[PDB]
Amino acid sequence: MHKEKWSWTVKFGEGWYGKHGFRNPTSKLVNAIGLRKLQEYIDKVVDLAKYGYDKLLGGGNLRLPLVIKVAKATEKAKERVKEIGGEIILTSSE
Amino acid sequence: MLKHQKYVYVDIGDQKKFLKVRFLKSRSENNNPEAYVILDKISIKLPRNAKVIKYEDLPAEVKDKLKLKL
Amino acid sequence: KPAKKNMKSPGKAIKFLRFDWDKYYRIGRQERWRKPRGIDNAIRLELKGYQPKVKIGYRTDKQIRGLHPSGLRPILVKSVKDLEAFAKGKQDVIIIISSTIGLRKRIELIKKAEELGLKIANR
Amino acid sequence: TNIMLRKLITSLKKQDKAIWVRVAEELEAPRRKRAYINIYKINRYSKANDIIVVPGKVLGVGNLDHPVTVVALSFSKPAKEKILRSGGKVMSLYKAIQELNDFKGKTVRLMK
Amino acid sequence: MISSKPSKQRKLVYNLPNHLRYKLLTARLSEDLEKQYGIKRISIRKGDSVKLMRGSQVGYEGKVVEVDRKRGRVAIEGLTKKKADGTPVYVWVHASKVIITKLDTGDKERMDAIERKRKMRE
Amino acid sequence: KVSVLDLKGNQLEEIELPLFFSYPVRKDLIRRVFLSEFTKSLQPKGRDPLAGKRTSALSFGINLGIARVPRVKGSGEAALAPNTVGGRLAFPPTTEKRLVEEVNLKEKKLGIISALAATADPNFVKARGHRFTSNNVPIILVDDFENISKAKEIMDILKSIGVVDDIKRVKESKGVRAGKGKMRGRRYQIAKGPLIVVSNHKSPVVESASNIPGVNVVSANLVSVIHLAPGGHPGRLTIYTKSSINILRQR
RNA sequence: AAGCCUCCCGGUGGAUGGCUCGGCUCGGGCACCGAAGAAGGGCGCGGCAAGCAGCGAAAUGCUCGGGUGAGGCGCAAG
RNA sequence: CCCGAACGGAAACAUCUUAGUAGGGGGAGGAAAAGAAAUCAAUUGAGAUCCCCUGAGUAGGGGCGACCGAAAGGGGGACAGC
RNA sequence: AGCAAACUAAGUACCGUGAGGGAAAGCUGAAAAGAACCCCGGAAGGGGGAGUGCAAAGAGCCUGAAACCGGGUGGUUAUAC
RNA sequence: CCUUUCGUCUUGAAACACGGGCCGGGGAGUUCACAUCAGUGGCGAGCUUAAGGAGAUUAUCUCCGAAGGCAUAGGGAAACCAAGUGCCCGCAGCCUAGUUUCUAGGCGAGGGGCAGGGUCUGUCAGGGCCUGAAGCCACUGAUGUGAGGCUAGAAACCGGGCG
RNA sequence: CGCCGAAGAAGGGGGGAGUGGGUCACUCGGCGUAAGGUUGGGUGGCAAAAGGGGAACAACCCAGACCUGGGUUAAGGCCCCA
RNA sequence: GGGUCUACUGAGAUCCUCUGGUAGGGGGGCGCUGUGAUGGGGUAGAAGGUGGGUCGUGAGAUCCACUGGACCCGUCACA
């Protein structure tokens, strides 16, 4: 409403007009999972494929060094897993 | 409500005050006291469809409890 | 006890009828009170001598607020059973035998009071 | 709105120890902002055999280092199991009144 | 399975089709009646006599002389209330407050209806 | 801790009931449940959508004056207006309106216990004013109870442990309830009576007692507040059997 | 002299209050008729008969079985 | 199953929407329609159609304005195929 | 009010040349026991008196408010709101 | 003794403005859905069952049914990347002795301020956003939005018929 | 300095509004000679403020109505109305 | 309004203080009709109407005489 409610545009209505880029229609779905949450399956070898998780997010901090094989993860998680004693298996398949 | 004749008003001196009790068409007698239960409701004016009884009409046995109120 | 009547008689209550009840019969028989929510209306403006608008300040004293006019406490009854729960005793309350109770039940009902020393108004 | 919940409030204010009274207005606070605690925080700010009073409910997320006994008005059935296996103790406010150690304990802190 | 709304029920009794009118006639027999008949209740027919238990004229025995089948009430002789002119009109008393005293065994078609009610032999 | 009673009326065992019966009698939740399920049985009412609308009525326009007001009239007579005769209502109720008050399954369940426990306190049972000569409430019947068919023998049992008073108390059917309901089926009102819960249904006693006023037979794995708190004043007198209790204890 | 006001009484209107063989919603059942003449109308028909309803010049009902079981001759008492 | 509206909305209004509804014409039955993939989707899988709940105001369309608006899959019902 | 429709006919009377629009209107008590009979008038379920019946508010029939008007009760008026 | 007639529109305008003969009966912020809040309760890193099935004295009821949706991580268009700790002031409460009566000091939840971290962008400073572990469900309530949308009120236009 | 403050609380967040035609008096302007005109700055009512005086009165002065009662006072007035 | 006591959840004592009023917000209370109940009860002597006492600031409640001639309230919760 350019005429009288145009004030709502500049405070509460940014982007209410026009378009902003396109989207990718084939961006692969990512099952991101938090390391903090992982102290459970779900309340030794562990893999997230059976739980369907793809990328191991940084999460919090683990408590026990275990066997971790997943699709992918972040860098900071990897050293953390190595730090405690666990290991990261960057297998591209189950 | 008086038209049911389930009440009877009392004439005393036929003056400007009247007394009322509940009469019993049963009990089959003129001397039956129990067919009459004395109340205490003096009334200023004689009601329209009222049924009137004379004080002397009462059985002599019941005059006793009444004349004192007269 | 002597301080029972010494505010009601001087503090003469006001009928508090509806604003402009006098003119139109369509109000008088209504015989109640309302709060005039107008603008040009008078009593809402508090102009002198117009049965002034009701306000909370005209209460009765809490020592007797809602006391029976005989000084006792007014509590009603509806059947024989309610009598046993008379509070404390016959010394501070009075009873109003039902406005609708039947006499063939009243005759026994009334006798239950004076034997307990109660006070009965609608005798 | 629980008859018990109001009833205890009548008793909590009665007791004189300064900790109990503070519970009431946290309790009388709105329900929608009522006190509540998740486990993971209390483990991070406590010592061994600490007594802590929770003005609300305790939620079961986090792990426990050392057994500690807590006093509250509401628990999560899972959360309690985390507490017992950790060796602590649970204690209702209502039951907590009858304890002179609750009267004269030591090292008590209040969190939310 | 039939309904229980008051309205529908009353419709049946205000609209009773003809071959169901016995329903508002059957009245209680006496013990002596059932003693040799083995039956509690039965529909009224003419030529009979009855006794009464309710009303200002309780305790009468007469004869079944008049009936209102469509709406269900009867009358008996020797019981009238004089009109202004002086001719009698029949007092109307419902079967609901009566006890039968005797019946007519001269039909052979009312008889078998008695029989079929599992009464013992004869 | 409660005693055990027979078909005759002599105490012969004693057990402490499962911890449910001690529960606080949380009134508030009960009503918020006793109401909730009761919402289900409101067959959606509604005024006719096309009531009074069967007209072509219209205003006579303005400046007529003789048409005093923009009231709408049909070629000679006024109708269709919300304010006047016969036309459609201001805001007619329709079946589209919501009726039920949903409760979570868990939320319903934990509430149900309260009424069950409510049957334990001798204070609360008299709070509803149920009259009963039994020294101990509630009352447990040895599980041979499930094998009665003749209805009359039921009475002596309620005579045995001395419950006949509330039977008579229900027997004071309050004549006729006021209002139109007398011509809408609900021609009476009756005080609720003793409640019996049995372990299994289809037992002979399940149907055998539906004659005594105020009483009902409902299976333990089924019974809820709608039987324990008729009126949201829980504490109605209740009866149980040993076998039934175990069926309860499993929650 | 008018009255004025209030009240008692009466009539003039019938709201209130009560009662309901009526409708309204729901759910569940059931769910095509027609050239062998439909549905829809128009006419007639009873002792004394106007409307409705039913009936079709075989007009308040024709026959045959089945049930029913003492009165019937509708709405609606002569 | 063919033909096919304006009123309003966009604070105006013409594209758009209101909308294949109001309505016209034809033709049935107690249900009608449809019904055996030139279907999907995608790691080599499922297996008629229909309706119900979701998917979902998602995808996507339009003075990018009001607004319009799927499919796939999953979960239910009966699941008949010649 | 409840669909217009609960009533002697309701899409009926009717307003319209027409497509069409579209009404109003329930209660005698249980039993008519409907006031026989006597006087007035010609008559009127009209008057009066009697009678039925718990009750007659007995045909215009349950209960019966006001706006209204009439008789009466109680005050009260032609130097004055 | 003191006293401009009701309501409304209205700076006041109400008294030369409007609508107001009397009485009685009728008569106007409701429904749904969504969004958001409050209050209330149940459960809790989950919540929640819908649609739906089975049994039942049969629409009440009990069990089953996560189907799904919201939260549980954000940034950017994407390719992708992808955190949750560390300092300090400091409330209530607690402990300390005095309690002289107590900011006397510590502990300090919460909270506040500096931080830090993830992210895109900028060649660094920076700049934008996210990050300090709690929401979901249910009832009632309120308001906005869309549906006739408090009630009533127009010339209009169109379709199809009838003169 | 003075006042409010942990009985009743600087900042922060949140739910719900109506309000966008003012007028007049005094005072300092402008326009216009003027105007119960218009248009500005400040203050005050009124609007939504009764009560007493000015004869009656939205705005002028006194003065902010929980109620009843007693008393003393204000702006004004004190020959009669009173 | 704010600073002590009892009560299967509202009732008391004491102290200070605050007291015009539309647009608007908020707190609390009576009535109407139905549902569930309900120590409960009330009815051929109800309901309602008329007039009049008494309670309550009021909202209204409640009562007495008569009329009527067959069904009607109190409390809680709900719509």
Image (cartoon, coloured by chain):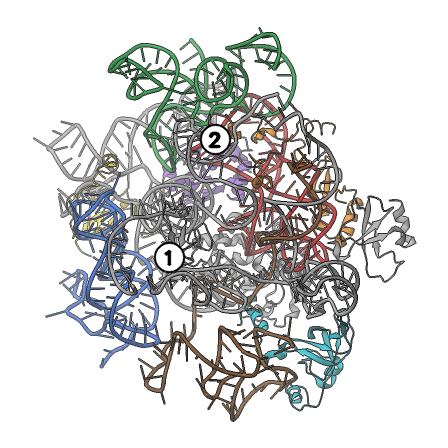
Chain colours: A yellow, C orange, D purple, E cyan, G brown, H blue, K green, L red
Query: Where is residue B25 drawn, in percent x and y?
Result: 81, 60
Residue A36 in sight from this viewpoint? yes
Which of the pair F174/D22 is nearer the observer? F174
Q: Amino acid at mark 1?
A: Ser
Q: Nearer the viewer, mark 1 or mark 2?
A: 1
Which of the pair D68/L23 is nearer the observer? L23
What element does badge 1 sit on? loop
Q: Which residue is mark 1?
A: F56
Q: Is residue K69 left or right of residue F100?
A: right
Identity of the residue drawn at 82% across and 44% down:
B17
Q: Residues within 10 Å of mark 2 (few under 14, many from 20)?
A: few
What quarter of the picture does the N terminus of chain C occupy?
top right
Q: Chain of mark 1?
A: F
Q: Which residue is mark 2?
A: C40
Which of the pair K14/C73 is nearer the observer? C73
What element does badge 2 sit on? loop
Rendered position, D40 above or below C44? below
